[PDB]
Amino acid sequence: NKCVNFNFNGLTGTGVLTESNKKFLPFQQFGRDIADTTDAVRDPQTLEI
Amino acid sequence: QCVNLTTRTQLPPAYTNSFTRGVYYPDKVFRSSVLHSTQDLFLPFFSNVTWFHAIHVTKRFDNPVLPFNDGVYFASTEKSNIIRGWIFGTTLDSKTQSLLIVNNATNVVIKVCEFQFCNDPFLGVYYHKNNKSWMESEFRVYSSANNCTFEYVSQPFLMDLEGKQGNFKNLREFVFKNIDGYFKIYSKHTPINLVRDLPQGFSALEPLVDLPIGINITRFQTLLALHRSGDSSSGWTAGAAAYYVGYLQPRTFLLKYNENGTITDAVDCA
Ligand SMILES: *[C@@H]1O[C@H](CO)[C@@H](O)[C@H](O)[C@H]1NC(C)=O
Image 1 (cartoon, each protein chain N blue to C red):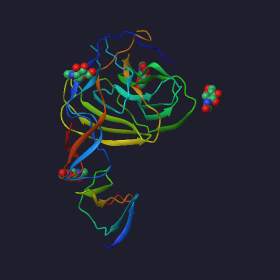
Image 2 (cartoon, protein in one colour):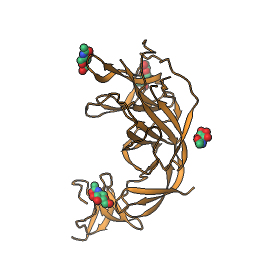
Image 3 (cartoon, rainbow over the protein chains, first blue to last red):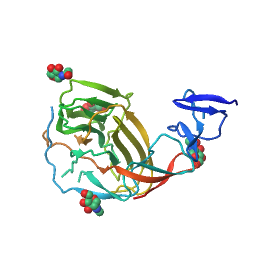
Image 4 (tube, each protein chain N blue to C red):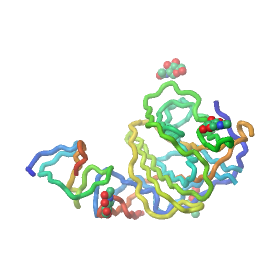
């Protein structure tokens, strides 16, 4: 809930992280919206999307 | 020690048609409700794949030495876990570094080692009439192995090994690729109710492992179990089993994802 510069397993970006209702598959790390812009990320430590 | 089995009838080769098979996730990037174009090594739709059979009825024991051009799609319609693993290399005689992936009765072995692979690698299961029980008895693949770097052994389990009767039930689809010095294995697996064919339909393979081996693979062979309960080269049964081999080529495919991340339809542009 804050503008944060984040780095998730080499994926670097800026933005606010919020709880998500999206359900990722076990083998999927991050999800891209249309146009291949990062939209969601699974934090590897606790596998929270 | 190895023995080259005899009592094996020679037939031509056979071939079959693969209907929209050999599709995996090209990348590890989750996409949901999207129509993605991707260029990569795929198995073309409505392709012809080499058919190898293992039937009791001859005994049709197929385990030839197949090339490995740029990747292989390997499907297996099995009932009693006859196919056990694979071997990949260049010369297979410990001159050059080979790879083997085996699934014996207890463990899953993955070695990248300098094996002196013999002409007829296989495994042998022994069946006891005194008390009906099947379990691995013989492991004839490889003679010697001196220099090697990469091993992996999985936590011991207990495996069926028993020979059922009926039609094939389990479809095992596997994709092997060797690129950037990475051996990439995609796998997936599906209950079937056919008798003799390799189903139609769609199913996207998901990646299973990425071995960082970086060897030079040009040929490979499958290795599958035989049943015993004759001589050293005659006393063995095959067991119902079939497996299909295809040969990946660089293609554009236009994949469809669901509202999920799972690939629910693809089309070959060429
Ligand atoms: C596709 O498979 C083989 C490839 O060697 C070829 O001989 C065959 O005629 C082609 N068509 C069919 C129907 O198998």
